[PDB]
Amino acid sequence: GSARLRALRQRQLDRAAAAVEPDVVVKRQEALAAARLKMQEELNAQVEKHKEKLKQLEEEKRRQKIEMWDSM
Amino acid sequence: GSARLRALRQRQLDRAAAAVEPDVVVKRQEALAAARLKMQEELNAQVEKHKEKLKQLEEEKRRQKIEMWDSM
Ligand SMILES: [Cl-]
Ligand SMILES: [Cl-]
Ligand SMILES: [Cl-]
Ligand SMILES: [Cl-]
Image 1 (cartoon, rainbow over the protein chains, first blue to last red):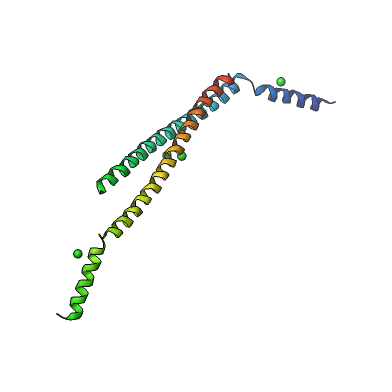
Image 2 (image 1 turned 30 degrees about the horizontal axis):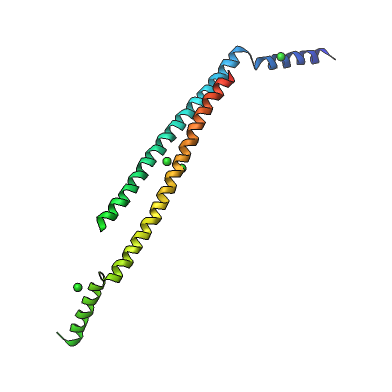
């Protein structure tokens, strides 16, 4: 071994432990939570868009029937 | 006037009346009804597709929540 290698190991240990230090853990959670919020906003907007489309399609179905009876 | 013009008028009258002759009326109705059936089949398939999408989006919303609680 050597002094340089012993220093390298210690720095690797510092890096390995840093992944789960409290500042890192909270920042990484905040990043995950912000991504989840964005994705929930997008899912919600899609849900509303599909509901609106279903409303419109039902109205077109009703119109097709009325139109027929009107044309008689 | 003239014989050719009197014949032309009579043929125009035949054409004008032909639009509402019974064979024409039934064939034109069958064309309208076949178009309506096609459009109703397409509306119905769209309705089912949007319902399926809504089902999937609701499942993704639920998954996002479970995943969070699981990650704690
Ligand atoms: Cl470590
Ligand atoms: Cl849509
Ligand atoms: Cl006529
Ligand atoms: Cl869809």
